[PDB]
Amino acid sequence: RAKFDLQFITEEGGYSKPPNVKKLMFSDFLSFLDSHKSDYRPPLLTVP
Amino acid sequence: FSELRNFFTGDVVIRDDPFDVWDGVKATYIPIGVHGVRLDPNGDQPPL
Amino acid sequence: FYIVKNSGFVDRGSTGPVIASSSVYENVLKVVHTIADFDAANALRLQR
Image 1: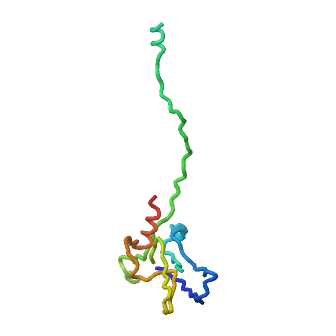
Image 2: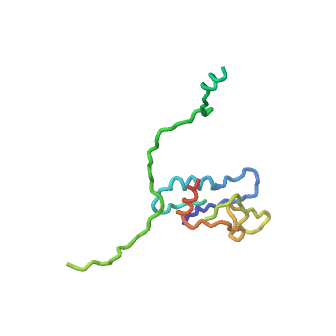
Image 3: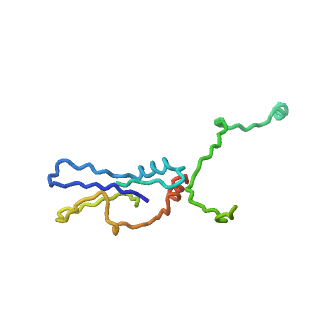
């Protein structure tokens, strides 16, 4: 089960400053599983 | 002289680099897995 | 949720409202492994 954090970005058309998009890496998922290894009921992953 | 040597001849085998020895370890166990709800097997108990 | 090597979605030149995204569309994914539940995902993380 997971929650997804939605975010909207408007592309004006001027390709000067690249937007900063939040990306979630595999590394982060492992870091998650290790902070909850002992939990006695599944934790919630917030996926952006 | 030969015989005197052959008497005082005996071999030994030793490890080139000494073993690296450690201390014991405190065997600590931690919880794992998720637990669900288990309902009583007999159901409601008789009155009084 | 899906785990994947790399992804994104750019639809340049489109006139639609969506032209980019941190994610992709479902039909573009090929599922080659399926992790059943939190437990199992956690279990795999621990088999070193």
